[PDB]
Image 1 (cartoon, each protein chain N blue to C red):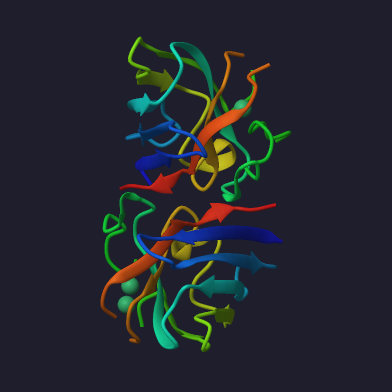
Image 2: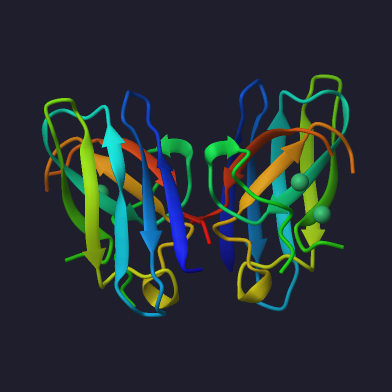
Length: 126
Length: 129
Ligand SMILES: [Zn+2]
Ligand SMILES: [Zn+2]
Ligand SMILES: [Zn+2]
């Protein structure tokens, strides 16, 4: 299976590790992990176009959209600020034109989204 | 992708930004930028297999060398008296597509010249254009 991973980092307490797995090229991508340091409640969760972190999350560009392909909806943080992520998505991919490897995963201040709290470049994983 | 970019960071003071450009598919890749916080001298400069920063550079995996010079071996960079390494390389082995694609993998700068010792800084190679 194709696998990817992303370490989310930002200016404040928000941080997380998100994993991706896709068993076949025309199949769904499993996305799972956790994000900490969030306000309790809903937060926008998107793939943005560029894997450019030269200005932190500011340089990631817009939502990836070759719904937007990059729109993975919202994640929910508990009372301790921890969001569990467990998503299966059939629009994103780890190959082809909807490929998100080398792009940026971003978690937002608000639900969908306000400021970009944390982000990371999506990389090939073992 | 015709351009990629990498922000190098580590546990210490080594930091940098490296650009990659490949205007023609399967063509030479231009690699350029600057790295600072280095000891004066030669430093190994490699693409490693995994774009996995979960444990900093320790999770970057081995030197990139698909069993279909390592593919990921971009040689050594030279830091000056101020600890700054200016990079301007052309490489025809790495690529931004295909079997030797380095998008989503990790760029690493080492403690020593290549035996290269610790990984001082690294970053995931991302799509820039
Ligand atoms: Zn967004
Ligand atoms: Zn969108
Ligand atoms: Zn190396």
